[PDB]
Length: 392
Ligand SMILES: Nc1ncnc2c1ncn2[C@@H]1O[C@H](CSCC[C@H](N)C(=O)O)[C@@H](O)[C@H]1O
Image: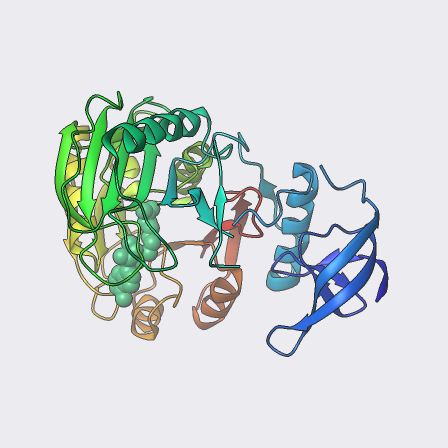
């Protein structure tokens, strides 16, 4: 119950002689007051910081100097994968995030702390100054139009979330008001952003997206990575760190070989479209219809020639490609896809993953070795990292 934190575990929690301590730093001198058990482990729920570590300044690592965050990620990857992996710093570590979902509740605007309690905020520094402006306009909108907001105790109220998105390289901003059934007052006199959306979440789930009801201004905003534009819709996924996303698409384009590329699990075509712009012959697949539709829209606005189709990893053919890129969901690569890759043996596989343990698992099953690998800090202030591996 007393001692110095020696390291962080893989979720970012301080390790003191096999008790866990959240938001602690190696080198912290602490006294553990209260313990609790979380999945058969002792977790320090009340502790006293006696001496602060010199490493100190979802953001569970935000109390740590950035260089130490990167050191923690290097060490974690080496533990999981078995060897040193370079970690590329995010070009920016505040203002880098291009989407935030703010809950709008009786007792404040921000996010759940103690799930029943809201943390009220005036700005979100990882998103940047646009959030301060949106929040301040939102308060005026709510106040002057007397808008009913979420009462979390009863789960009643009209307005639930304000989701803010922006293109870091285009300066376009989209705001999306997610509500229950109702009538949203005209938001046009309160916001000056390029796109304003009203979405109605008609399910019982607490979610920060819903059915598109109306938009004012642009139907889509854009983000731009180098010379490639990507349409952003309230309901479509896009890498959340625009600055690192630039390094990620460049890195993928550098690792592929040949001319014929498969962009497997393409989503909205982040890799495939960038590669088509660079002159590759690209086909991409994803099981999500809406994502594929966005990828097709992206092909059009960039005037490239690439094809995207909806298919499951259980069925996709990998025949006839020079490089196959895979960016699988949390489950990793379907076993049938691994069999197909083993049989067809494309010259190069590029595997992108923010789940190092699943990557490590799948690579053992593939008849390939790691030729090159780097991690990109896509997720500053969290324990997560994005790996990009070239397999041959
Ligand atoms: N069983 C399956 N078969 C094919 N696609 C799947 C799948 N399960 C999930 N997906 C898709 O797998 C993708 C993983 S995220 C991939 C991100 C994409 N490369 C981008 O840059 O934006 C998602 O787009 C998801 O819709």
